[PDB]
Image (cartoon, coloured by chain):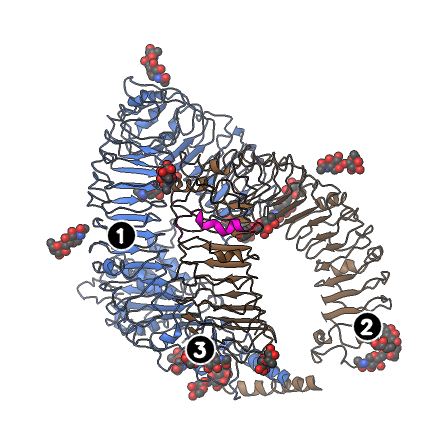
Chain colours: A blue, B brown
Amino acid sequence: SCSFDGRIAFYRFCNLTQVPQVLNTTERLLLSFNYIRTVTASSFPFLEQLQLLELGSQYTPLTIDKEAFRNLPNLRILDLGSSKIYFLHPDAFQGLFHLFELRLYFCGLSDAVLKDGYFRNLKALTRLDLSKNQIRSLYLHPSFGKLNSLKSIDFSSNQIFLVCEHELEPLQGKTLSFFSLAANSLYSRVSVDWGKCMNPFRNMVLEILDVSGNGWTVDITGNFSNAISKSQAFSLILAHHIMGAGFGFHNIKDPDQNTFAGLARSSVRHLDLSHGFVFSLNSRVFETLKDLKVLNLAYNKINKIADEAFYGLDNLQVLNLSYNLLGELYSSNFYGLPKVAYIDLQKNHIAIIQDQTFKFLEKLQTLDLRDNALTTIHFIPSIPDIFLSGNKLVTLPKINLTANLIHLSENRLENLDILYFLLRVPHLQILILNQNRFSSCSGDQTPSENPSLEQLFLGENMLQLAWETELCWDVFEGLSHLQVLYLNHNYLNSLPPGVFSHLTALRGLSLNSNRLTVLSHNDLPANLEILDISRNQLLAPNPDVFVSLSVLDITHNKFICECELSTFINWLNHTNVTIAGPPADIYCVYPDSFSGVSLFSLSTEGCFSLFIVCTVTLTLFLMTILTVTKFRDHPQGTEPDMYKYDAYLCFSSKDFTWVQNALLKHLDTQYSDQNRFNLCFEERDFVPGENRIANIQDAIWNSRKIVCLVSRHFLRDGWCLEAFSYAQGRCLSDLNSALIMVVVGSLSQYQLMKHQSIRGFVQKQQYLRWPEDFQDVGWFLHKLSQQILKKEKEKKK
Amino acid sequence: SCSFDGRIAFYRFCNLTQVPQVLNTTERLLLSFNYIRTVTASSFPFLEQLQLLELGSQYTPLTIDKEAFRNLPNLRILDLGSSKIYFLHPDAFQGLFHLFELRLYFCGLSDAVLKDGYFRNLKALTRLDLSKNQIRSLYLHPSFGKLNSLKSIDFSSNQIFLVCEHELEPLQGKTLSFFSLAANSLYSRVSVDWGKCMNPFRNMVLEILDVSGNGWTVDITGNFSNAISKSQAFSLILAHHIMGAGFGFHNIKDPDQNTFAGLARSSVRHLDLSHGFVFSLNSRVFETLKDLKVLNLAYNKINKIADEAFYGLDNLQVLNLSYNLLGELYSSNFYGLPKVAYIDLQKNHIAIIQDQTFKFLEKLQTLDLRDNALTTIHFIPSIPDIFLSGNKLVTLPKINLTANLIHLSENRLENLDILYFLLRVPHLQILILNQNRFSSCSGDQTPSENPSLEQLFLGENMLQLAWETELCWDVFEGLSHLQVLYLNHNYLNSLPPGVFSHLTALRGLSLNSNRLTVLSHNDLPANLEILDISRNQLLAPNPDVFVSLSVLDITHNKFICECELSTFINWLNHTNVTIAGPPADIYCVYPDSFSGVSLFSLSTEGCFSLFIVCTVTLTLFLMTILTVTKFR
Ligand SMILES: *[C@@H]1O[C@H](CO[C@@H]2O[C@@H](C)[C@@H](O)[C@@H](O)[C@@H]2O)[C@@H](O)[C@H](O)[C@H]1NC(C)=O
Ligand SMILES: *[C@@H]1O[C@H](CO[C@@H]2O[C@@H](C)[C@@H](O)[C@@H](O)[C@@H]2O)[C@@H](O)[C@H](O)[C@H]1NC(C)=O
Ligand SMILES: *[C@@H]1O[C@H](CO[C@@H]2O[C@@H](C)[C@@H](O)[C@@H](O)[C@@H]2O)[C@@H](O)[C@H](O)[C@H]1NC(C)=O
Ligand SMILES: *[C@@H]1O[C@H](CO[C@@H]2O[C@@H](C)[C@@H](O)[C@@H](O)[C@@H]2O)[C@@H](O)[C@H](O)[C@H]1NC(C)=O
Ligand SMILES: *[C@@H]1O[C@H](CO[C@@H]2O[C@@H](C)[C@@H](O)[C@@H](O)[C@@H]2O)[C@@H](O)[C@H](O)[C@H]1NC(C)=O
Ligand SMILES: *[C@@H]1O[C@H](CO[C@@H]2O[C@@H](C)[C@@H](O)[C@@H](O)[C@@H]2O)[C@@H](O)[C@H](O)[C@H]1NC(C)=O
Ligand SMILES: *[C@@H]1O[C@H](CO[C@@H]2O[C@@H](C)[C@@H](O)[C@@H](O)[C@@H]2O)[C@@H](O)[C@H](O)[C@H]1NC(C)=O
Ligand SMILES: *[C@@H]1O[C@H](CO[C@@H]2O[C@@H](C)[C@@H](O)[C@@H](O)[C@@H]2O)[C@@H](O)[C@H](O)[C@H]1NC(C)=O
Ligand SMILES: *[C@@H]1O[C@H](CO[C@@H]2O[C@@H](C)[C@@H](O)[C@@H](O)[C@@H]2O)[C@@H](O)[C@H](O)[C@H]1NC(C)=O
Ligand SMILES: *[C@@H]1O[C@H](CO[C@@H]2O[C@@H](C)[C@@H](O)[C@@H](O)[C@@H]2O)[C@@H](O)[C@H](O)[C@H]1NC(C)=O
Ligand SMILES: *[C@@H]1O[C@H](CO[C@@H]2O[C@@H](C)[C@@H](O)[C@@H](O)[C@@H]2O)[C@@H](O)[C@H](O)[C@H]1NC(C)=O
Ligand SMILES: *[C@@H]1O[C@H](CO[C@@H]2O[C@@H](C)[C@@H](O)[C@@H](O)[C@@H]2O)[C@@H](O)[C@H](O)[C@H]1NC(C)=O
Ligand SMILES: *[C@@H]1O[C@H](CO[C@@H]2O[C@@H](C)[C@@H](O)[C@@H](O)[C@@H]2O)[C@@H](O)[C@H](O)[C@H]1NC(C)=O
Ligand SMILES: *[C@@H]1O[C@H](CO[C@@H]2O[C@@H](C)[C@@H](O)[C@@H](O)[C@@H]2O)[C@@H](O)[C@H](O)[C@H]1NC(C)=O
């Protein structure tokens, strides 16, 4: 099983009938590599909370009866992969109301025609997949008309030879409906129809159109381009064929001219050539298609790049050149792409990038160069974010203010390319430097000019000898990451106190996997929440302790447990458990006799054992069964009746910003995993079956208390339903702890209409107003967590 | 210190001068993560029986003087790793007579040229290593001529651009000397010399030749393959480059035909492609090389294999295909490998193996398939030994007499695959079955026909309900291993006496971690030396005792130290100390007052150290209910 109570998997166990042992709350069920064959009615009346029900995977089903999936309303998707169904029953998929996708990969369609298909009662049917089938006719059945949510379909590996006009009637029937027609993928078609009254693709807007391998020869694939004329399609991928680019080159230099002749009239926006194995890319390829807003080239082997190659693209935006470089490069790649913005040159084998490379550009706002090249920045436009990982030594950078994001992982940098790069990016926020193997660290000429520096990781790297200078002297909110910096403790003994002096808004410093001997403590910062210290050789105490410190990781370190240092072992004990890390991962090293004991067990004695270990286990057994009772909200299971909630939160819709961020989060954070402090709502947990006013009525009985949030808006339409209820039937008295008033905002007097119950709970004056200052934020949470846990007043007098 | 008197290790202690506290008999000294810098004469006149003296590891040695290692004749190896020496003194390594290997990993050679090197007085110098250096010239100094014991050297991460003929003169001087030239590994070379009177590798037999990453482009690397022509090399690894196989494919389809052109003349015997990241394996790769006596493909990612893929290999023997499977498989992989014998398909991800897989084979004598596939034996030739572990349910086996060794660990077997597989292996000797989780145990249809059965371990498994039948009725010298078999004590009561009946030449039976209630004793075997009995719930004595029993393990068991069973507690005593196990690990369980006391301390009476703790625990359990309800 993957997850307890929810996710259960059964990967090949050879069962005959379904598994009943599973619970009814199982949301993700997986039955594959098994056999059931005959699927009779009432198959799964057990589970009713399913979503991911991957049934069909080589389950070799022979037939399918009706009422198979009747008790599966919340059924999201169903994957009938590699199945062999012969008989298809009309009312088999009945009851599936929330069915979106449906994978019918190799369902064994011996009954090719889709007319007999039964996907009419599937309105939420979005992505209906049909691959590895034997469909002969592309003729869309009238049932597609009802399919409004139908967004994508993948017709691949079927058959379909001719594509008449009459086979596209339901298409023109819908005025607004996206359609990712992924047909003609790995087929054996021959010809199609053209002309007629209206072209088969005339007055028809499609989302996506794939033609991954259509014909056998270039001569028969030209007629098809004459039928796709006058068609408004977003994308159009011509993959698995084009081995070379050019004026209009595909295979043979003679019939390759009639191809672009039909796509010239149509205004193509997106053109992709993935897995096309384009060796050479001749001069001027996309010239007829200037309306190409976005292009795509994934997994290729480009080598011929002319200065007139990308010409024609007057308005390009996106362009992913993923794995298609290597084999030298020239100067000025994109000379005709001023409006370019996003480019993805991930995973390549470029040697050395020249100076003038990213010439004639301006609107470039995102440069992703993962494992691209040796990187040489000189004429790189205003790009806010850039990714440069998996590289080597980098040369002088050249960027501007616009750069607010930048990444550098798994590299080999120096103290030059980092200084100048930061000199003009005060808008920088996130920055990463993991496993860069820093060579030399300057005194203060590397991380200069960067006030808004938020994230800054310096893990796995080396410095000039050891840390002995302050680099972060201008970084206020600098969250550093010092993981194994190979720092020699000899120079760390006289560590400059002016390093952790400027840092005032530090969230947490992580000094782990390091190699120090004396753990200095400069508690100048006051916003430090954590300090990870593990895999070290520390053994030195310090009276100076931070104020906001809470979680101090100090596990697995060379601790000397003898009579020499008794002041250090004394500090860690005085710091209570509230200020310490897992005691379980702390053992003494130096001691040969005693090895594997936590510091919170060693005896502080100055330099009969069976009695010692027998008395201490008794003293342990004297307190551990005396403090768990005392130490360990109001238990719902001990309540007289059966209440489901602790407090019903009554509020307004305009004041959701507070009830959703502060109130709920501060009352749910405690005993969250224990699910003890539950809150009743009116929109999160309701009954459609029920009435508005009464929805609150039931919430009163179920909840232990009622904590409303009176406001200048809560009176406008939140009290209009409450006051009316108090008139007829009474429930909440005056001086009872059952009701708790909370004033989030001062409410005037003119707002109060003729309601007599609103001014009744204000007369008693027992509300909990929201403090204005931030220092008072806590005294409110105290009482807000008290009055509710308070025992309700009894009925007797 | 690792071992008393001999092995002492000082891992990061920060000490200027060497540790004088060590003894003279210290054979293994480890001084790393420290600092000494100036190494003056008479460094270690204390220790004189050293062998493993790893000195240099980031010890940042600035300079080195003479007479440093004078008092270290028995000094075997020295590893100066990650060091930074500037000045090299000629007579620095004097006195080393038994110095074999020498690791100079990143010694910081600011004085690149090796002419200034001083390794003449080192005759025992076998494996001289020089990695991560800055050597520019491959020119071998005349000093190599004296190095007769010089077997291997690793020239990696240096510089070396051109490899002339004149840089390979000391080689031709020696008529008999193995040399594992591991040069050109991660360099930045460009070209070499060709033609001339004689080729640079003409009339020169080498043991090993590594070229892990040489050029930058396929074009410049083709010149190198034309200079290595006519060379008698035992091995030749082309690693970290070939991302695809084929008729002679490497990178670009045009300049990859001139590669095999030069290696065609030279008769290659060993060809390895480790860490090559070979994805696709086209048809017919090694065709020009038919003299390849042995092959090797370690750490690769082979998706699919063609039928004519392994074509060309006429006389193959060894073939370690370690971690390079997954991605479906076809029928008849090695159709052209009759003479193949040893193959290593360790660590792979194969779903199911077809019927006809090991077709056209015969001289296969050792099949190692550690964590290979679901294993489906059908057309397997005469293979004496085979290793099948880290697998799942195994189907009907098909082997012959030739199989004398077989292993099965960490699996899920039944009573079918073990029966038939044993029906034709009377020559079997060793057999392991640790953690196989046996499903159903047959009465006598599983361990049949196997007289020469020597080792037979049945640790961690299950049987039909419990042990209640004699399986080893034909196994004479069968050394069983019964560790935790989940045997229910209810059926163990009527344990068939005919189980330990046939077993006469038994060395020792291990009945540990089990869960029996009564310990029976059928002393029929007269050769049983030992009988491990621990982690059980036994409490039954028996007059029948073996004769050759010496060590009887009987610790950590549910023993009832009361007045009920007095005959059992009286037996373990008469059996003397010579026939017993560690009394220290024997404590009473059932009792609550008398707890934690060895059977050889209990008194036999009819119905004082561990007594005071039983009284102080009561007094503190009485004085507590008193002062708790009062305090807080
Ligand atoms: C999973 O299925 C196992 C196999 O069930 C059947 O076993 C015999 C009787 C044959 O008829 C075979 O075709 C069947 O597959 C069960 O033993 C097992 O109990 C099942 N798991 C559950 C739900 O307990
Ligand atoms: C699993 O769920 C089964 C069906 O539960 C309910 O049955 C009736 C009472 C209706 O209220 C219906 O809406 C529900 O589906 C139970 O019969 C069964 O006891 C459950 N399994 C467990 C946990 O016992
Ligand atoms: C492309 O279409 C061309 C014209 O097809 C038909 O030719 C005659 C039979 C007319 O009467 C009418 O049916 C059409 O105009 C073909 O000559 C050519 O072969 C086609 N290309 C292919 C698919 O091979
Ligand atoms: C850039 O292109 C990326 C890859 O696109 C495709 O992803 C799948 C469907 C493959 O099977 C293959 O055909 C392509 O590689 C996208 O993930 C990314 O969204 C694209 N950039 C944009 C516009 O966001
Ligand atoms: C980076 O910015 C340089 C300076 O641009 C501006 O100069 C004057 C006009 C002021 O308005 C000032 O605030 C600006 O900083 C440009 O000269 C330079 O071309 C830019 N770098 C690039 C992308 O070439
Ligand atoms: C150790 O902890 C002592 C108690 O701290 C807290 O005291 C009140 C406010 C309670 O809410 C309680 O639960 C807490 O444990 C401190 O008085 C003492 O200063 C601490 N030791 C140190 C590090 O000085
Ligand atoms: C745990 O620490 C105990 C108390 O620590 C401190 O002792 C003195 C020096 C006081 O002035 C005050 O700071 C604290 O109360 C020790 O009594 C005890 O032995 C320690 N436990 C262990 C691990 O032995
Ligand atoms: C190990 O070395 C310890 C100290 O050695 C050095 O002492 C001075 C000269 C400083 O430069 C210091 O940084 C060095 O670490 C000794 O105290 C110790 O006794 C030595 N270990 C032994 C052999 O007992
Ligand atoms: C270690 O050995 C030192 C030298 O002892 C001997 O000196 C002359 C006589 C030679 O025969 C030489 O081979 C011998 O090693 C001693 O000074 C020293 O005490 C010894 N260390 C110990 C074990 O105390
Ligand atoms: C490989 O060698 C090519 C030409 O080989 C010879 O070069 C000199 C010695 C001439 O005088 C003549 O003997 C030959 O033509 C170069 O064209 C080629 O660039 C070299 N490979 C590299 C490093 O690119
Ligand atoms: C079979 O191959 C085994 C391991 O292969 C590799 O050995 C060396 C070169 C290392 O690079 C290692 O990482 C590899 O796994 C050998 O142990 C074995 O000797 C080879 N078979 C032979 C011929 O004996
Ligand atoms: C296993 O052995 C079978 C029998 O081989 C022999 O048959 C006659 C000729 C006698 O000489 C007898 O002693 C031998 O046992 C073969 O038929 C069979 O092919 C072998 N199994 C394999 C590897 O296919
Ligand atoms: C150890 O055992 C000694 C011998 O016990 C029995 O002596 C007679 C009565 C025979 O019947 C024979 O079966 C046994 O050997 C005791 O005398 C001695 O008390 C024992 N030691 C202890 C634990 O007290
Ligand atoms: C117990 O051992 C008795 C004699 O003890 C042995 O005495 C001498 C001769 C040495 O061999 C010494 O090692 C022995 O401990 C036997 O008389 C007696 O039969 C043994 N008890 C049993 C198990 O029957």
Mark 1 is on which residue type? Asp
The location of residue A23, given as percent across then percent down, is 53, 51
| Circles 3 and 2: CB atoms closer than 8 Å | no
- The quadrant of the rendering that contains the C terminus of chain A is bottom left
Q: Name the subunit of mark 1.
A: A
Mark 2 is on which residue type? Phe
Instruction: Report which residue position mark 2 lands on.
Output: B568
For marks 3 and 2, the one nearer the N-term is: 3
Question: Which residue is found at the position 70% from the left and 63% from the top?
Answer: B513
Q: In the image, is residue B498 part of the stretch drawn in magenta? A: no
Spatial separation of the CA atoms under disc 3 and disc 2? 66 Å
Q: Are labels 3 and 2 on one chain?
A: yes
Q: Secondary structure at mark 2?
A: helix
Q: Residue B16 shows which numbered tag? A: 3
The location of residue B553, given as percent across then percent down, is 75, 69
| Circles 1 and 2: CB atoms closer than 8 Å | no
Q: Residues within 10 Å of mark 2 (few under 14, many from 20)?
A: some
Please give the count of numbered marks on the rendered protein: 3
Q: Is mark 1 within 8 Å of ligand 4?
A: no
Mark 3 is on which residue type? Leu
- Left or right: A459 with respect to B287? left
Of the pair B108 and A202, the residue shown nearer to us: B108
The location of residue A769, given as percent across then percent down, is 27, 70
